[PDB]
Image (cartoon, coloured by chain):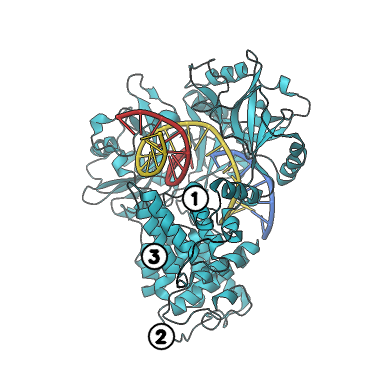
Chain colours: A cyan, B red, C blue, D yellow
Amino acid sequence: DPSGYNPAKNNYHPVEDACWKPGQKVPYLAVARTFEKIEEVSARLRMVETLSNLLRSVVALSPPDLLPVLYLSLNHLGPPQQGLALGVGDGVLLKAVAQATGRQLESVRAEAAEKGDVGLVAENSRSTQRLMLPPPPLTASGVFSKFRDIARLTGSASTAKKIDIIKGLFVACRHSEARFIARSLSGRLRLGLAEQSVLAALSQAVSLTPPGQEFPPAMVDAGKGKTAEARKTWLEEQGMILKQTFCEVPDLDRIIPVLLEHGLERLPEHCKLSPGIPLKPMLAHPTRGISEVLKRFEEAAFTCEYKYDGQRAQIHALEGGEVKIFSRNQADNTGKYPDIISRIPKIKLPSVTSFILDTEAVAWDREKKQIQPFQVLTTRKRKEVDASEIQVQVCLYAFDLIYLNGESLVREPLSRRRQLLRENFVETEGEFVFATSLDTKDIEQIAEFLEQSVKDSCEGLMVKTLDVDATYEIAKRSHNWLKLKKDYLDGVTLDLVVIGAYLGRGKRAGRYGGFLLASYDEDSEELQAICKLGTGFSDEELEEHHQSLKALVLPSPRPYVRIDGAVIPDHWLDPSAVWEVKCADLSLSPIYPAARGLVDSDKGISLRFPRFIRVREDKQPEQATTSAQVACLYRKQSQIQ
DNA sequence: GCTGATGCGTG
DNA sequence: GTCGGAC
DNA sequence: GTCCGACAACGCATCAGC
């Protein structure tokens, strides 16, 4: 019985401790009870084992339902390159919850804000939907199919059609199913388990309970014959095989069929890196300064590169001539860059048949022959058929080569990948350029190069080793690079007034999760909202922010507080607290009124990546950073005149 | 035909 | 994107 | 360090309401 399913018990038997018969569809309550056991605990090992127990039962009893259960665990709809999106957020969901309970929409919205969780609202509310006959229980594949049905709905009256499907799921929910149906649509499962733990649990499940066995399975626990130490290293090796394959082919529609037909040990023999299938890109860890860089990379030659402020572009050229371009998150952006497709013959040598390039697409002004800010790049359309219609040109800055002429370079050091990149590809100014580099170990040279990058309209420097641990194997370390930005360094900020608070969600439920900040306009003697603040404080600081600021809650805002298009705070705060806030950039804002009219007639100024530093107990709202000072900091930037 | 609200997605 | 928590 | 989920600004695209 799925109501009593406990995948966290000791000595879990994949066949007898499951809550469904062989060949039957996996009930969605089995996935929900698994979610309950996973979110209760905080150790990833315990969460992996709990999920692994569910997956073993799916492997042994209902193999066809392995894919939907995995996607439900990841809260995804399919492969990232397929570009499926629900089209449902908190807006559609709370409306579906309201129509299914007869409550006012504003009441359901207010309760979801107080509890910081929409699933709790969908669970503690009473249904007003009446059915002549009881509905069949939800299944894992059925619930997954309805999710994809929602994502396929487009056109006029499609919103109401989405809500009907959501109402149909709610009317069939049992126990904790409504809570997790709502969380999945809201995109906040609050599990504590994501992609890495799902992969770890998958490899552990197919290793302990091998797929493809005739029922009843003879091998239900392949680790019982091994010592704890032997069991540990074996599962770790098997986990790396799956993780290394998934990083090169993040497509469960491809891995799972191969996994079920040929096992995990033979998986790299079928799923291999190849152009046309996006791969997980290499990421970077922050570094607080140059001294920290020489410590993390001490005793290893490294290179320094400009960190261009654009969008990543993973360019696949296939055997035959087909070109595809993928974002960092494996989204297919080929239709977005017809200008890049036309550029491919100009950048490669005649001996180049196929490749996978790692580049940064940057908005480029061909009149001034200079780099344009990130905001200009985002103004490009999402579908451009004719390249002549393109208004914002882009210049590609290449910095890595992952695949070349039928051969993978994942296991090659950076020094050789960079060697192959610069030998086999041709530069064209303003179109396709190699990233500005510097190979050195001196502190002063790196400091000058960092300052030269900021002057050249870049975020700072990327630091990458050349030979030691310098491969492109994300499964070994996905953040193998270092990023050194100007705003990372101590002493290289604004003092803003807290004018509002926002109820927190998930880990912030029950307290404040965000705050509305404001600068002081000297000319009008008003506080102008500049940005929201939601990170930088510790749990201890935020709990004390919740206790003291609750004493400054107002029914109505002060007449001298201006927020314009900003989100109205759940709790208006009497202006008193002043916080020191750091940001990466100042942007011209479409909503915030801070410093409006001082640099632009219509738009005020906001803060890119704002972060809480410390409380400014010495200053009152009258002494906060002025709006005029905000305008000065904005014009001081490179790309702003 | 226009527009604000909502969703998606990039940093 | 930044950040801190739990491990 | 790793993995995770809190939270930020701001752009295009879609759809309902007008």
Between residues A239 and A632, which one lies in front from this camera angle? A632
Q: Amino acid type of disc 3?
A: Ile
Quadrant of the image occupied by residue A388: top left
**Residue that mark 3 sits on:** A255
Between residues A301 and A325, which one lies in front from this camera angle? A325
**Residue that mark 1 sits on:** A95
| Position of residue A171 in the picture relative to residue A626 (left or right) | left
Quadrant of the image occupied by residue A515: top right
A523 shown above or below A57: above
A131 shown above or below A477: below
Between residues A355 and A297, which one lies in front from this camera angle? A355
Provide residue A61's location: percent of width, then percent of height.
45, 79
Q: Local crowd at mark 3 within 10 Å, few (<14), some, or many (≥20)?
A: many
CA–CA distance in space, label 3 to label 1: 37 Å
**Residue that mark 2 sits on:** A214
Which badge, 3 or 1, is on the more N-terminal residue? 1
A252 shown above or below A524: below
- Can the viewer see residue A173? yes
